[PDB]
């Protein structure tokens, strides 16, 4: 996996 | 919202599962006929990957057909390679199939495939 | 072949197009009912993203239903957020919805969502 | 984009 897009 | 988190591998995981559904012939709703040769697929994936299928399946009459016959000049191997690319992101481009793949991608209106085919041909000149 | 080239953005481009089809209500083939609230979707995308929908639409009788009613304990907002995640890879997780999102992801059998929900809850303890 | 996977 999870990221800040 | 602008505060969403994103799972990086999600799109690839979905595509992998759609290809497993195709392999197992699950919820396939169209047969594409290319000369002698029949290919079962999901209309949504074909529309998502091709300007030709997007035009076909958004037509009020053709959206209902369960069989689509392609132009007899289309090569079944070229179509097969492009159908695999649609469901996997991998294109099996080889010296012996590049002309047929490019002609099929032009017909199917797959812009990115046509561009790479052109680049590989230009490098071989 | 082991000699394929790969278009990096393909899976994401397909998913974007499937979400545009959903927005425009094109070739949607199921309505998911969550209490008062109805959501139109593509059975293939739901199966690709959820162990629950994969079990439902591979069943010889349920594969034919055009309406699926979820358990009345399921929160429609939680379902809506998960349906958007399925079609976009982006999860709108907020303090005010995380419990409902996690309970809905457990019911729908979405493993990656459940794991991130658990991590965000554990950080808030 | 195109890469060697
Ligand atoms: C996936 C990526 O490589 C693009 C593939 N592709 C091309 O090359 N053309 C010309 C397309 C032309 C159209 C489409 N499909 C769509 C375009 C607009 N809106 C929606 Cl909802 C779809 C669908 N389904 C894909 C095309
Ligand atoms: C996309 C990724 O996040 C995984 C989502 N997901 C989960 O979490 N479970 C438990 C699934 C359980 C099942 C599935 N769906 C499939 C699994 C096997 N073969 C096929 Cl063809 C599909 C389909 N369609 C997705 C699941």
Image (cartoon, coloured by chain):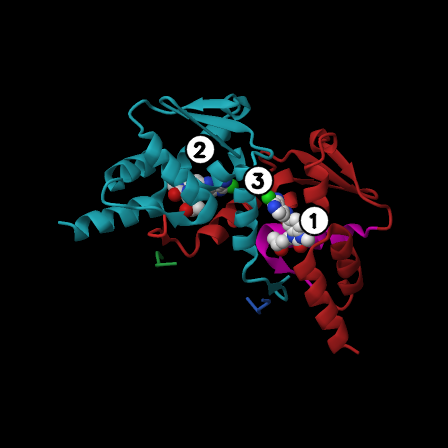
Chain colours: A blue, B cyan, C red, D green
- Residue in the image at 69% along x and 55% along y: C110
The residue that mark 1 highlights is C51
Residue drawn at x 74%, y 30% is C61
Measured as percent of width and height from the top left, residue C81 is found at 70, 55
The single residue placed furthest to the left in the displayed view is B125
Q: Element type at marker 3?
A: helix
Circle 2 sits in a helix, a strand or a loop, which is it? helix
What is the span of residues highlighted in magenta in the rendered image?
C74-93
Whether residues under marks 2 and 1 lie with C-beta atoms below 8 angstroms apart, the answer is: no
Real-space Cα separation, disc 2 to disc 1, in angstroms: 29 Å
Q: Check disc 1 and report its element: helix, strand or loop.
A: helix
Per the rendering, the mark at residue B53 is 2
Task: Confirm if mark 3 falls within 8 A of ligand 2.
Answer: yes
Q: Is residue C74 left or right of residue C8?
A: right
Mark number displayed over residue B21: 3
**Label 2 beta carbon within 8 A of ligand 1:** yes
Query: Is C119 placed above or below C29 here?
Result: below
Vertical placement of B76 versus C106: above or below? above
Chain letter for mark 2: B
Q: CA distance from mark 3 to mark 2?
A: 19 Å
């Amino acid at each position: 996996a999870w990221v800040i897009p | 919202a602008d505060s969403c988190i994103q799972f990086t591998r999600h799109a690839s995981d979905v595509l992998l599962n759609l290809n497993r559904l195709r392999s197992r012939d699950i919820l396939t709703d169209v047969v594409i006929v290319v000369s002698r040769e029949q290919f079962r697929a999901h209309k949504t994936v074909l529309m998502a990957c091709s300007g030709l299928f997007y035009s076909i399946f958004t037509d009020q009459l053709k959206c209902n057909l369960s069989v689509i016959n392609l132009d007899p000049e289309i090569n079944p191997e070229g179509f097969c390679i492009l159908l695999d690319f649609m469901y996997t992101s991998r294109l099996n481009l080889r010296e012996g199939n590049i002309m047929a793949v490019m002609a099929t991608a032009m017909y199917l209106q797959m812009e990115h495939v046509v561009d790479t085919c052109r680049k590989f041909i230009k490098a071989s000149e």
